[PDB]
Image (cartoon, rainbow over the protein chains, first blue to last red):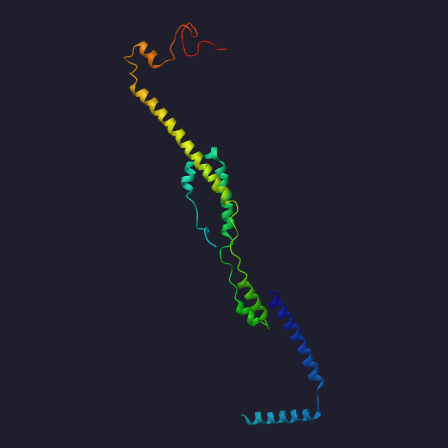
Length: 53
Length: 161
């Protein structure tokens, strides 16, 4: 039970640490060329939903 | 590991009939004292509680410590401890046997005395057609010259003080 709770405590802090690391890394990594590509994909997906009727 | 599981129990009924109740009231203490150790014998059976080692192996990231714990648990399997005062009980058992034989032969002697007394009463002539001399002969309490005098020679007419 001690090893299980130690593993659970280490798993919980690693999950919390990787969550805030991913949030900070995703927010700090914003590029305009990828933003325009995602904008074009959103327009194409909107056009695909209009066709799907 | 063997010998006495909780199923073993001597016949209390014959033992309870044998003792003279409050004359051997320590048996009433002894049975409850033994019953208390039965309560300890009620708990902790032979095998312990099984543990699912595979659940802890899969849940823990590194199950090598669980394997080491399981290997050490299987290696450390201590057997039963040693009997201490069994020889003293055996020594008192032999002393009890001697007291058994001594009490048996003394009771046999007293039984033969009571049988001889009943044989005397069986061979005694009845009190209806019995002469007074034969009453004195069958019961040697008697009266004679070196005897306590009394106005009526009775069982206790002499001192009365």
